Structures are given as structure tokens and as C-alpha cells.
Image (cartoon, coloured by chain):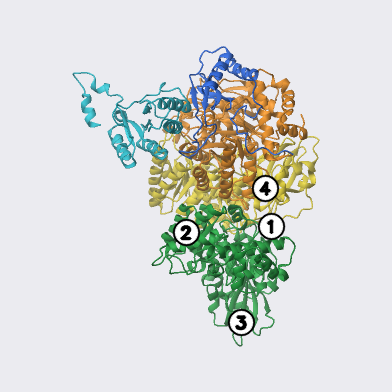
Chain colours: A blue, B orange, C yellow, D green, E cyan
Amino acid sequence: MQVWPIEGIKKFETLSYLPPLTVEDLLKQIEYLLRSKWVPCLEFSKVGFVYRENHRSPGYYDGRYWTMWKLPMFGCTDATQVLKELEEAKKAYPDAFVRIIGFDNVRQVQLISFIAYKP
Amino acid sequence: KLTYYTPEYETKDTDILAAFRVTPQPGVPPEEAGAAVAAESSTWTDGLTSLDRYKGRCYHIEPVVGEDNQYIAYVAYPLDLFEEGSVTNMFTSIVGNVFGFKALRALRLEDLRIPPTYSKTFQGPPHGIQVERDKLNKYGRPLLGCTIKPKLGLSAKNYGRACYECLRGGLDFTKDDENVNSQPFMRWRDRFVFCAEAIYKSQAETGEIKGHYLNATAGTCEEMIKRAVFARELGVPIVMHDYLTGGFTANTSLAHYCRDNGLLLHIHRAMHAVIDRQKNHGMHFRVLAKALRMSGGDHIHAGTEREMTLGFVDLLRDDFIEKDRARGIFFTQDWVSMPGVIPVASGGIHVWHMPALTEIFGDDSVLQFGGGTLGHPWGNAPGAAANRVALEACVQARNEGRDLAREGNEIIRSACKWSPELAAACEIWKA
Amino acid sequence: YKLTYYTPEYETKDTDILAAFRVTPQPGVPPEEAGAAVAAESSTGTWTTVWTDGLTSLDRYKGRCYHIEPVVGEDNQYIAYVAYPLDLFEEGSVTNMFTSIVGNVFGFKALRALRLEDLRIPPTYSKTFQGPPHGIQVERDKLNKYGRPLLGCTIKPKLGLSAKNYGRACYECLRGGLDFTKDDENVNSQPFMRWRDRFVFCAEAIYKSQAETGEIKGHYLNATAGTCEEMIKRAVFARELGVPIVMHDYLTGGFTANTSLAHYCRDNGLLLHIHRAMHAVIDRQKNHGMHFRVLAKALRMSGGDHIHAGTVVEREMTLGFVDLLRDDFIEKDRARGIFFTQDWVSMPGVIPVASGGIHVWHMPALTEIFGDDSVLQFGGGTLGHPWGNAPGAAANRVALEACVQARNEGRDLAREGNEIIRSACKWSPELAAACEIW
Amino acid sequence: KLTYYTPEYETKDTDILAAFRVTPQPGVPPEEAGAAVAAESSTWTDGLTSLDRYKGRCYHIEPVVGEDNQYIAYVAYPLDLFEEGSVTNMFTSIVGNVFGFKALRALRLEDLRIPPTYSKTFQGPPHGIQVERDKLNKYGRPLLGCTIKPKLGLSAKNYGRACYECLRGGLDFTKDDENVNSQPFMRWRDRFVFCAEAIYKSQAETGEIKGHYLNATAGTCEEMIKRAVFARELGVPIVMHDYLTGGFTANTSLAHYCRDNGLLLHIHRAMHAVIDRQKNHGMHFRVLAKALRMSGGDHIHAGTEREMTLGFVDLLRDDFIEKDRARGIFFTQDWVSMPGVIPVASGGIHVWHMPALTEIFGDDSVLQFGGGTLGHPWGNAPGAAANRVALEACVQARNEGRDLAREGNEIIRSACKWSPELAAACEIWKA
Amino acid sequence: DKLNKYGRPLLGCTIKPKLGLSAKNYGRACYECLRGGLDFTKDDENVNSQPFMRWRDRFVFCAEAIYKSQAETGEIKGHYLNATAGTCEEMIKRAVFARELGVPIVMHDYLTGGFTANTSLAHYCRDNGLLLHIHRAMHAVIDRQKNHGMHFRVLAKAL
């Protein structure tokens, strides 16, 4: 019997219970967005998790929004371009978390978010 | 045939349409049975108005292929018969009387065409699928829940203890059983307090937003609202209602409260099988599902034959659903931007069912693992981790282009190689 | 397993809630397994073991199938008796009682069909319920009406009347001798007639008819609504108008809303007429659902002063749940569908309301079958009178009172009914006209 | 004998049963006296009903052995006589009139069989023993309290100063004296403010949850609820009421408020000895204790002859209590899962009484040390530490299998060797 | 004085598209705008409560954007949360939640809402410390033609 850890495995929602993603596995997730006609975008933050500083009413949390890296990559067809921007963000903010998100113009929402880099 | 069988009537865009599965008594022609369904579910004082304006009319009858003495009767009800925003009155008007008519041996309401003109008088879901995902910051996978077992018998503290371990292992939600309201040995406010502590301890530990379906089902509307009020004070994200046993008048009141106060509303369909199980009599679940979307709810339990389920899943989630008899969709349903409801899958599922559930339902679903979490040999947190790992292994494989229908067992076995939690789960429950 | 949930030597406790299910197992499922499954899947059944069970004593929370036997009803049907511990149920909540007992078990795969036939509500549970806002005797005392069935009329056309023309029909029916007129179950608030306009004109009709005749009059004003707030708002205006009775569709409105309305009616002196709209969705088929006597017991607990109870034109089954609705103590009598001895420990009774195709010739049978503590509702039996609503009401009041007089004298209503009516036709031209067309 | 002496009447499971200790006047036979107790405590207009349905009946009479002219009369009252959920009406019905009957020289109500059918109409304790332990995270020992002395004469600030030192030394609770409500020189809101600061300072310092019985006893129900409301705003865990001097109508109202708002309710039995002291007349405390459990309270003062105390302690705490005349339990009492009330021991106790109190009462008790804490030569915090040390030394020894009845003094002397606080306490108070 | 801003015009930005964004994506745009140096973002005069973006959801996400941008920059931020509604009850309900969220400013379309409602909302904002941003939607129906109507200066004095 093994005890589930209490520290050091804080999470970032979808895919964060998998082992750290390789570059080829990261490319496959990015391609999934492109195949699905969704727009990839990068997001970064020095704070990795949600908190409740300004209010505690139902459905209010701080720390859900991170900061946008540049703009959503509209019309992107090359998944390696997303990787190039990921590496750029890692260079400018080596102590920041970076996740990859996705937007759909059809259902008009954000529908993807998975962690791409931890400092 | 009568003044109620009008086989060339052209439905109006404001009409509420109904598809009844009618089984006439011996010696009752289907034309006569269909006119009776329209009459018995609608209509000197008659000279003081125009009855043809207020009658339901059976505008089409067809046989059920493969069943003798079974027919589908289509009936059109004028818009003026229904009170705005009241599912209670829609049910009263359409199913309040006709199922007892002696000329009908059996009767089952299969579907309802809710016209946009009527549905726009309903608030609908307090939030719906897309708002809920944004509020909870969760994207790209089914959500995970777990009903606390035993139902009753635990202290309020031991109950919340189980919730914390479940949530900290990777589940998004834990759940009050539909039976858990307020009872001797676990009063509701005590449960709300300890479950609140479990919600926030697990959220601080993992970094992900957590919730617990706090059941507000009560004997009176006053008690029901009192329980939602305390959940609001505690700042938690979601409450719960048994909409069929509580009733539509109470459910619509609670849905209005949750909209006004930012609460997600998890809906359990307790007692539905009393009504929707038999093919020959009752009301199909898709009718009870449309009613819930109109009355208001953010989740609804949908079970776990597969084509019928996919049919009303689309009717619960999508904006526009084209007619499809193969999937039990008798009417084209236009919801004119009323938000959708997240279907909740439950029923003896475990890690090995994750490929099938992920492929069948897609991301916009909640998968509920009661015994599939609390039955893990290592406890609730490893059991949650096993379920969360199995799900994300399936999501990753689907996103990569893999076929969860033929590779599902291989995908689960592959994740067993690095997740001891999943490996232990897969050892007790078999493929 | 079987011996966890099939406990045939279990002795029921006086605090148990007992259920009698009519079970149709799937082919190959023996009766003892079907019985254990009904109890298990309506209590503590789990498909896999959970460690949390070690934190409690589950046997104190399980339902037990303590008896199962075949019934002469159709293919492969049995009656399974289940006992539920008192601690399972929230006090005062019909909603939780239904959820706890019928919430899940009807969908179990091994059960091809399932129907709840009866419930034994123990005094320890029924005492947590207010019950009827007033009940049979309080209602008779409030209305000053004794010694005969009460009389009502359903206003028709059901929909399409203006509020004022609705109240005009009500006044003419009431002034002729009927005690009540009735909002249709479908009549709530609609484009053809908004509820507050109806309440206003129906109140004028009530008081005009009462002042003309000198007898207390009422009209079931339907408070059924889409939200509990709208429902209470309609009850509040009826309270302001000072009228005696309001109305609720308890099944489509729901038990949570109905219990709230019953509490309001008790707090404000309003009688509560209850309609059973949508009951046949549930209670029609012999093989699956819930018999009406279960829904009738639940209404008496949640609260109502009248309840619609159907017609007699099967009788012994109807007489069974009439007794369950009216009496303080009802002995077990399965021939009338009474599977459990039911003790209501002084919870008031509900007046059953007979309705469906009833006209003047049926008055002897109705008075004999139901006795004085009933309401007899007429549809076309009043409005279809060739002389109008007031002569139609007079015909029904005359026919009823001639039946009551004859019964009081010791005459046999089941055999002398036609001659009692014909004899009354001689001095009531209103009744004669009704008997010429029906 | 009369229509009220029915010596073969079989009690109903819904009957309320009473055991009276009756002392008839000279020349009044016990059969006649017993019928009078039933009649005088119950029953042309008589022809409009059935009096035998509403009469109390004396179904059994027996002598009191060792007392001349004393008898126990057992009376059965039908369930319909009592208003649901009203201890006020139960007392009015049973003890409202009969104690003044001239044919009875003296009368004492000894016990009451509260049928489950009647007790289920009462909320009961706002929380009860098990909920309270879970809320406070305290297990495996009696709780410790201390009434602030002097009763009156301290400023509100100096009052709270004493509370802080007491709590920081190891006590779980401090206590408003039953007399302390609101008075010149210490108004209640000022006391609530300073006691709140003392509660949270001591809790932050020690890490254990602390409380203070903030007395809400008032002249009107409006004032009483106003004081509970501010305690709720301050977020403190427990308030207090003098249920006999405040009254049952007010106590039930306050108990409902504490249930709705998560407050523990400490109940003091002030003025009980006016009623329960004399063996020949009044009402035994066990009757007042059952009434409090029904009306509502989480603690109740129980005093510090020992068999009678153990009797009503079981009646306060346990779910099912079998008849036991040796311990004054005249009736089998089934509480059908109504929570129990923590008995509070008080009365000139100190560290040397810890073995006896721990063995006699067990863990589910509060031990109150007023002078036993404030009388310590080193102050309140060392006095609390002395009491907490003595208690845990007793608990440890009991858990190890030792006999606190014969080793208690040795256990206390042994703890003196390492706790200078206890040694100083044991020097001023002797074994 | 309330906003601690002196010596320059204030800067705002109406979120576009008007309608079509989710409440979350709407607030996402607000955060990026405010963190770059703007004092305010703005609900379009048309943005009240609509299918796909109900007002309370927008208020929640815009509140998160207000406080994230304020914590990041150190300057006080706001968003004109539009309280324009079909009834005065709905209008006040929306100002009440903005008050609970603790944000500095709300918004009203005073000509289309009407003066009776605007004066009621102005009284509420005075009682509760809220700044009131006023949009003049439909003014050109009245003030455009030189020969007929009411000049905007009259509508401005009235406001």
C-alpha cells in the first residue's frame, strides 16, 4: 500500500496527472488542437494555483487567469511554431509556469488548458 | 376520427408538439385512439369561445414497426395553453389526464417539441456547460465525481473525511447521495461544515478547484432554500437537488436562487425509473431531461440502448438537434442559445470503463466513481488518483488520434506501468 | 448477497417503514434473489466493497426483504415485503421518503418490472408531518355543512374562458345548490386568463352566490405555479380576499412545494383542495409504477384537505384507499389493496373527491359507496343541464338530498336508487329535466 | 378506586407514562390516591366526546419499601393530550395541577416514559455529544471548564483576562456564571467582546480549539436571541442558557437558533434544587434532565446517591436505557437516535477528585474547576495546567488498565513528580 | 481622490466584440487591457445581460480581472459594469452585486433606462460609494438635427 503524496505534486488540471510530457508528446497535443481547428495560445504566471484573496462568494476565485503570452496563434498550421514560442517564454521567464490553452471560434469559448513548463 | 384527428394540420412554430406511443384497447382503431389522446389531453359555455383554438389535435399517426398494436400519435398543442416558465403546468397540461383514459390500454410520452417561443420564457440552467467550465477553470476532459458511501451511517465528520481524501487524489467533485438530506446522526448543517473544510483543504493541497454536491433536497421549499443559503455563505461552488422527488415547482425556485447567487446546481434524477423504464407506458427520460433543462440544472444524471442515450445527451447539451428516429429524437429541437446541461454518468463503473465512457460521452460529462473510488485497496486518495490517471491516459491517447474503442485496454495497461495506483485498481476490477 | 438482504425470519419493528413491492424478476432470477435485490438496491447495496463500511454498522441501515410470495397477478409476479429503518428518512419529508424507497430500485436490471403497492408509515415517522391543514371534521365545522356529501362542479371549457365569464359560470353553479366550483388542474395563469383576474371575479361569484342562498360557498382557486414564490403569492391573495379554499396539483407541482403550501394553508385558515394530475403516468399499469394508494398516503402526510380519488362508474380498491385517506386506523385487507395495518394516530383525514362521467342517476350509488364524507364533482353533469348551470346544480343537490333522506330512513340505495330518483323527479322539475336527457 | 384506577390497562407504545411518588393524606387508600393522581392530572359537554380516550389512568400502584405511607403510582397519558415539540405543554399537562390536590399530602414526579412517537416531534440537542466532539476535534478524555470568579465585581476586561489565562493553561472552556447575564459594571456585549479576544488568543497560543460559555439568559426572548446573534457574529463555538429560570419556551427557541447557526449550547440547571431536592415532593432531576434533552442543549450541569446520578447520566447520554429501579430508572427509555447531552460535573472539585470523576463519568463529560483553577497559588494558567495534567495522568492510567478507584492517589502523586504545577495544586488541596 | 489619480486624463477601453465573447474571455480581455496601463475597461452600452453572457457571470470574471491587474501594476483599476436593465429591480440587483464585489464603478444608459431609473441608481451609488459611468445611448435620436429636438447640452445638464 502506497500513500498519495501531500506535497510536491500540485496540479494544473488536464494532463497534469501524467508523467512530464516529452517534446514529441507535447507536439502531439498541439497537433490535436490544429487538427480540431482550435487556436493555440500560451499563458504564463509566477503563481501556479488558485487563491481567494478578493472574495469568497460561490464561483469566485483569484488565480484562474494567467498572463497571455503574445496573442492566440490564429491560422497556425505548424505545431513546431508553438514549441518555438514555448521556448521563447521559457527564456524570458524561466521562473514562470507556462501552459498551453486553446480557443474555438465556433462554440466561442476556451476549451483547452494543459501545463507545458514548470520552473 | 373526430374533431381531434386533423391529419393535414400544419404545425405552427409556436406549437408544443408531443409524440405519444399509444396502445389502444382491443377494438379501438388507431385513428380513434389518436384523436382521444389529443382530446383527453386538452378539450353551453362552449359557445362563449372558440374550442378549435384551444384543442390539441393529433395531426399524424404511424405504426411502431416490430410491435403489434403500437402507434406513435403526434399531437399539437397551441401556445396559449401553457403558463410561461412553468414546467409544472406543461406537464399538467400534456400528461395530467390522458394516461388514465380507458380507451388507451397503455400510453408513453416519447418526446416533446419545445418551441423557442415557449423555451424563452424559462431561465434554464443556472450556468450551463461553458460557464461551468470557465468558473472552475477545467478544460479538455470529463470531470470526475464520487458519491460518498455508505449513504447513511457515517458521522458528518467521517463523511467529510472521506470527501477530503477523494478530492485530494484527483477527483473534481464528491457527492451527497440522493437520499442524503438531513437525518438522525448526520444533520445537514453539520455535513455542510465538514464537507466545506474538506473542499478547501483538498483545493489548497492540489491547486485545483474542488466541489461537493451539497444536497439541498428538503421537505419544504423553505428548508430547501435555507440549505442553499448556507452553502452560499460557505462560498462553495455547487449544490444538488433531486428534481423529480422534490418537484418542478421547488426545482425552478432553487434554480433561480443558484442563478442569483453563482451556485452550480447538480441534478439527480431519483425515481425516474418509476416513470421511464417500461417501453409501453410512462414518459421517456428524454422528456424528463428536456424538462430539467428548462426548469434549471447544471448537471443531470444520465445513466451509463447506447443510441437512445446519445440521443438525449445531445438534447441536453446541444443548441440545435435535428430529428433522428434511430436515436429516439422524434422532433427537431431548437434551444435558441439556452445553455446545455452536463450529463453525469454513473452505475458500477471503474477504471476499465474509462476508454468507453470517454469515447461515448466526450469531454462534456461528469463520470461518477462511488465504489470505483472508495473500493480501492489503498484508500480514497489512491483510488481517485487511479481514476484521474486512467482518464487522462485515455484523453491523451484520444487527442493523439488513437482509437479508444479498440485500444482502450492497451491504453489502460500502458498507464499501469508507471502508476502504481492504477495498477492496484486494475488488479481488483477486471477488463 | 441473499442472506444479507433476504432475511425471512426478521420480525418487523414498530418503527420500521414497511413496503410491499410487486416484483417481476427477469427470467432465471429466483424469487429470493429478486427480493434481496429490491431491498439492497433501495438501501445499502454496493457493487464493490468499500472500507468506509468499517466506520459504522451497516446492518442498522439496510433494508430487509423479510417475505416474498407469488401473486396470482399475470406472469411471474411476486409480492416482496421490505422493512426500512426509521433513521433513514428525514422527518417531515415525503420527498425524502420517496427518494429513499423508490429513488433507485425501479431501474435495476435483474427486475423486469416493479410496482410499489403499499407502505406502512409508523407513528414515529407520521408524527413528524403536519398532515392535512384542517381535515374532514374541521372542514365540516368551518363550512357548517353536515350529513351529506359535498357537491362541486368543474368549470368548462377547461381553457379559453375569460376570467369574468369563468366567474359568471361559477356564480350560476354555486347559486343553484353546489358547495364548490373548481379551477381546472390546467388553469393556473395563461394568456387567455391571468390568475389574479380569475381570483377577483371568482371571489365576486363566491360572495354573490353565498349572499343569495345563505350557505357558505367556495371555489378551488388553483395556486399551482412554476415556482414556490409564485405559488405562495397566489395563496396570499386568496387569503386577502378571504375565500375558504385554494387548490394545488401536488404531483406536477411536487411534494416540496405542496408541503410548503399545506403549511401556509394551516397558518392562514385556508382549505386545500388537491388534484392528482399525472397520477396515471405512474399508477395505471399493474406491473410497474406506484399504486395510487401510495400517492394518496403521501398526500395525506404532505398535506391536503381534499384529494381527487377517481370514479366508480375498481370499486374495492378505491374503497381501500378511501379508508386509508379518511380513517384513523385501517386494518390489513389485501383484497382491497391494504397490505399493511395503518395507524394514523389522530392525523386528520382527507375528503375524497369523486369525479368522472357522474350524473344524477349515479347519486344513489355514490352516496351508498362513499357515504357522507366525500365531494361529488360534476362536469357536464351540471353544465350540460338543458336549463343552465343553476338548474343543473339544483338537480344535483335535489338528487343528492333525496338519496340522503332515503338512506336515513333505512332504504336500500343500491336497489331502490332509480325509484328514489324518479320519485324526486316528481316535485323537482329541475331534476326531471336532467333525467330526461341522461 | 374509580374510572381512573385501571390496574390491568396495557400501556400503548405511544402513551406518555409517569411514575409519581404519592403520599396520601391520612385515611386515603393508595388505590384512591392513585386514581386521584390520574384524574387530577387529566380529566353535559362530556356527552359530546369520549372521556376514556382522554383520561390519564393509574395502571399500577406499589408501595415504597422502607417508607411508610409512600407509594409509586404509574399513570398512562394518551398521546393526543400533548402539543408536538412543546416541553412546556408536557409539563403543563402532567404536573400543572395534581400537586395541589388536597387528598395528596405530598407528590413527587420521579420519572417519565417519553415514547419515540412523541420525542420525534422535538429537535433535541442542537448537536449532541458526538457532533460536539467532532466540531471541537477533542477525543478520549473529559473536557475541562472553569467558571470565572468572582461572579460579579470584575470589569468586562478583567473578566476576559481571567478567561485567557485559564484557557491557555489547558482548559477547554471558561464559563459565565449562571447569574452573569448583563449587569451594572459588566454589560453583556462588553463581556462578549473581551471573552472573544481571550478565546482566540488562547487558541492561537496553544493550537487547541477553545470556547467560553457566553450566557444568553435574558429577561425577554428578544434580548436572549440578540445575545446569541452577536456570539454568532464573533464566530465563537458555544453559548449558554439557564433553562429553568429562562423557561422552556425560551430554551426551545434558543436551541432552534443554535441548531440553525452551529452554536453549541451549554445548559445550566439553576433553581433545580427548588424542585428536586426533597424526596417526598417535587420532580426528580432525571425528569428535568429528560425535558432538557427534548427541549435542547449540548451540555447540562449534573452535579457531583452516586447510583441515582449514574442513572440520569445514562438517560442523558445513551440511546436506549433499560429500566433499573436500583438507579432510579422507572421506565425503559428509547430515544430513537436523538443525540445525547454531555453532563457537566461541578461542585468544589479539585485535582484530587480527578481519578474518581474520570472513572465515574467517563470521557463523555465536562469537569468544571472554578476555585480549583482560580485558587491555584501560581495563577490561572498554572492552575489549568495542573488540572489538565491530573486529568491526562488519570486517562493514561485508565487506558493502561489501571484501577483509578484504588490507584487514583498514587497516580496523582506520580504526576506530581514531573509537573510542578500539579505538585503546587496538591499541596494546598489534600487527598 | 478616491482613485488616487491626478494630473492626466483617465484612460478607458470598451471591450469588443460587444457580444459574442464568453464571460470569461470577456474578462480575460479586461485584465490584459488594465495591466497595460488603462484605468478602466468598459461594458458596451448594449451589454446588459444576454444569452451566452449573463450579467452575474460577467461581473465575476471582470472582478477577477480588476483585482489581478491592480495587484500587478499597483494602480487602482475599474470596469464600468453596466447595470442597465429592463426594470428598476433588476438594475438595483446588479448594482448590489457590484457593491458586494467591492469594485469602484458601475454604468447606466441614462436615456434608454430613463431618468426615473437613473436618479434611483444615482442615489444607490451615493449611498454605497460607487462611481457611476453614464453612457448617452440614443442621444442622436434627439440632438442631431439643428432644426428639431433637444441639444445635447440640455441632456447633459439633466444628467
How far apart marks 4 and 2 lie (CA) works out to: 57 Å
Residue beneath label 1, please?
Answer: C14
Residue beneath label 3, please?
Answer: D23
How far apart marks 3 and 4 lie (CA) works out to: 51 Å
Query: Amino acid type of disc 1?
Result: Asp
Residue D285: x and y, percent?
59, 71
Residue beneath label 2, please?
Answer: D195
Residue B331: x and y, percent?
57, 23
Residue beneath label 4, please?
Answer: C118
* Residue A104 left/right relative to C388: right
Q: Under tag 1, what secondary structure?
A: loop
Q: Which tag is nearer the camera, tag 3 or tag 4?
A: 3
Query: Are the residues tagged 4 and 2 within 8 Å (C-beta)?
Result: no
Q: Which tag is nearer the camera, tag 4 or tag 1?
A: 1
How far apart marks 2 and 1 lie (CA) works out to: 49 Å
How far apart marks 3 and 1 lie (CA) works out to: 37 Å
* Label located before the other in sequence (2 or 3): 3
When the figure is inspected, residue D131 is found, relative to residue B167, above or below; the finding is: below
Q: Which tag is nearer the camera, tag 3 or tag 1?
A: 3
Determine the residue located farthest toward the bottom in the rendered image: D26
Disc assigned to residue C401? none
Label 3 neighbourhood size at 10 Å, few (<14), some (14-19), many (20+)? many
Q: Which tag is nearer the camera, tag 2 or tag 3?
A: 2
Q: Which tag is nearer the camera, tag 4 or tag 2?
A: 2
